Image: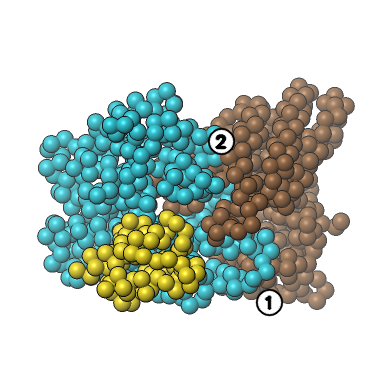
Chain colours: A yellow, B cyan, C brown
């Protein structure tokens, strides 16, 4: 649901139209995405859900679509 | 949960502080309200390490080593330990707090930096030997935050690299910081007193300068620090049209690389400001003082500045540079009103 | 040429001002100050907000010309900011007692072809009276652009008061009020011979030092040890060679290469100064009648070959060019210590 919104947000950032993206796909530790993609994700969260402070910007929070969805859920109460 | 911060060493110190019952972000960082513009510029010739005019910001003030030492009655000591004493030092420091152990980025597999020692050395906190003989290392930088395993031989190799561009050779900060029972009982009293003192320092708005082999270093504290910083940063407006060109000379490519790095470094200081201000608000809440400041949110104002900085170093253009200056001016305004209201209640 | 020059702008500028008051800077002031120092900026006590990177360089400037020029002349080399409506009167007042290094951005000096950047550091020029059309004559002290250039009074005031002002040059003058008294003028070659001994003794004393600053811990080492320590430290940047060889660099890895190459460019510029300074010492020694006793060693040539090696490395960051820079620096170090010992014996 958020996971659906996160997967929708990420697909157009990937290296290829056919890049496999599941809820457990590694995004940053794999160098699939770089920090210009992280900026797009931060800016999407800022405008759609609850803006994230620096303490939320961790590889544990951002490395998979499931982790991003969990981050937005946790931070949107 | 591993504690962390926008600066690796602060994250590391927060983990060590928790071992001895000290909440570093709230009682040490959050108790030290600060705002400083720093400049390195041409002073008296010769200054062979002055490579460029440089400007940044700091919300660290005197810094956690000074405050953590006087608040605990302990010591935070820098040493280059001989290899034959490193492991004994790591075991000995653990009784009374712990150690920040420096190493190159390329010694830390989780940094994905095999091909470079990085601009500066990294730091970790050794957190004991596990059942299998391997060291547990705490990573205190928010992005990589967590616990990692390293073999003892790999740890010693990391402490004594060859070559050693950063001079990491047995470099430790030993935190012998365990408070007495009577001091532990009063940490929030000391935090209250440090909070008032830093607020008075801020309003005193001292400035200074020093001539060094790396340049004249100038600093300015207090309510005008961020206005002065913004006025100075306008001097880097040339980066916008220069970063848009696609055919840059080696020298112009260096100007852009160094200019982007100035805003990257600044952005990490803005992240730290948001972290520190959040600590201040947790401190004020726990002291029962949240009443007298109302709902002012200097943490949120600095968070907005940090985001403007990230946008600018990621894409150097005039709109992004103007947005950073606006966010910084807003943070300056919220800071001075918050500081004045809070000191009135102390 | 009609104008004196050096590999550092401000040194060339100072040489022109010194000549006005009967001081040969390169021979009597730079050449009288034998020095060799390794400098490093590294991590020290937190926090250090201006420490952006570990940095290593070299200097043969020692205490530097402002210190030596001021004490040898009995005058002053003083930095200050003056308001726009007092700048021209300050330039005339300084001229009556020496001269001025006037700060300005690179982009204000058309002869530098630097319109699109204020550069990493500000520039300096020496005001040198006016041309027949009333334009100010500006001496360029850097060898690469050596000469005198005209700038209208309106343009010179616009250059001295830039907006914005990244380098803080606004109305900044380094005033060289350096004309020696008649009595002091007659003592200059005596004071130069004293300074020459005193720097060689400082070099052989090989002191070290370390300061903690908001820009890092600054470590230095003087003397015969200085170049060997520098070479040992610069080996830490061997990682640049494989990195600059790779074709697809992240913004991050591009930055690391750019900053590393800039470390070698700054170092190369200090090798040019060493060659200049050593040549000055050889001139000072020749004029004191000591060249025959001291012998035919050429530390100037050894530092010039180190400079060429540095430029070669700056153009192509490869392990062979790095090793060639290290060999050149080691050879310069060996000539320096043999020369220093033979000269100090004859003084």
Viewer-side label of 1, 2:
2
- Nearer to me, B203 or C257: C257
Q: Quadrant of residue C151?
A: bottom right
Is C327 placed above or below B13 here? Answer: above
- Determine if residue C91 is in view: no
Please, what secondary structure does the residue beneath circle 1 have?
A: helix
Classify mark 1: residues with Cα within 10 Å, few (<14), some (14-19) or many (20+): few
- Horizontal side of A70 relative to C167 (left or right) equals left
Chain of residue at mark 1:
C
Return the residue at label 1: C154
- Nearer to me, C329 or C298: C329
Return the residue at label 2: B163
Marking on residue C268: none
Q: Where is residue C281 in the image (x, y as percent from the top left)?
A: 77, 37
Q: Position of residue B253 (x, y in %)?
A: 63, 62
- Determine if residue A69 is in view: yes
Quadrant (top left/top right/bottom left/bottom right) for the C terminus of chain B: bottom left
- Horizontal side of B18 relative to C319 (left or right) equals left
Q: In which quarter of the image is residue B135?
A: top left
Q: Position of residue B211 (x, y in %)?
A: 52, 48
């Amino acid at each position: 649901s958020l996971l659906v919104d996160v997967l929708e947000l990420l697909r157009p950032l990937l290296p290829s139209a056919d890049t496999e993206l599941t809820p457990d796909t590694e995004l940053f530790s794999s160098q699939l995405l770089d920090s210009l993609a992280l900026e797009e994700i931060q800016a999407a969260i800022e405008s759609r859900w609850v803006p994230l402070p620096p303490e939320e910007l961790t590889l544990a929070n951002f490395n998979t679509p499931a982790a991003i969805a969990e981050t937005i859920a946790r931070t949107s109460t | 949960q591993t504690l962390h911060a926008p600066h690796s060493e602060v994250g590391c110190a927060a983990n060590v502080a928790r071992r001895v019952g000290v909440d570093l972000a709230r009682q040490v960082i959050g108790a030290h309200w600060a705002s400083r513009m720093l400049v390195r510029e041409v002073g008296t010739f010769p200054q062979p390490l002055l490579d460029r005019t440089q400007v940044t910001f700091s919300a660290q003030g005197e810094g956690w080593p000074a405050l953590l030492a006087r608040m605990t009655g302990g010591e935070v000591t820098s040493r280059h330990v001989p290899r034959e004493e490193l492991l004994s030092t790591l075991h000995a420091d653990r009784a009374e707090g712990g150690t920040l152990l420096f190493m190159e980025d390329r010694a830390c597999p989780w940094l994905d930096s095999a091909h470079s020692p990085g601009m500066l050395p990294h730091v970790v906190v050794p957190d004991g030997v596990a059942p299998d003989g391997s060291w547990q290392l705490i990573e205190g930088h928010s992005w990589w935050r967590g616990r990692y395993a390293m073999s003892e031989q790999d740890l010693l190799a990391a402490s004594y690299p060859d070559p050693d561009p950063h001079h990491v050779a047995g470099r430790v900060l030993s935190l012998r910081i365990r408070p007495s029972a009577e001091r532990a009982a009063q940490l929030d009293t000391l935090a209250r007193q440090e909070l008032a003192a830093g607020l008075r320092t801020y309003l005193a708005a001292e400035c200074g300068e020093t001539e060094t082999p790396a340049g004249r270093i100038v600093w300015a504290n207090g309510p005008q620090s961020v206005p002065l910083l913004v006025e100075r940063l306008r001097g880097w407006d040339y980066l916008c049209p220069l970063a848009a060109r696609n055919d840059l000379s080696t020298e112009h490519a260096r100007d852009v690389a160094l200019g982007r790095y100035l805003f990257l470094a600044l952005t990490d200081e803005l992240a730290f400001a948001a972290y520190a201000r959040a600590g201040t608000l947790r401190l004020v809440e726990g002291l029962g003082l949240a009443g007298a400041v109302g709902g002012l949110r200097p943490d949120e104002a600095w968070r907005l500045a940090w985001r403007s900085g990230q946008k600018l170093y990621r894409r150097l253009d005039r709109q992004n540079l103007s947005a950073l200056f606006s966010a910084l001016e807003k943070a300056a305004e919220v800071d001075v009103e918050y500081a004045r209201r809070l000191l009135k209640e102390l």
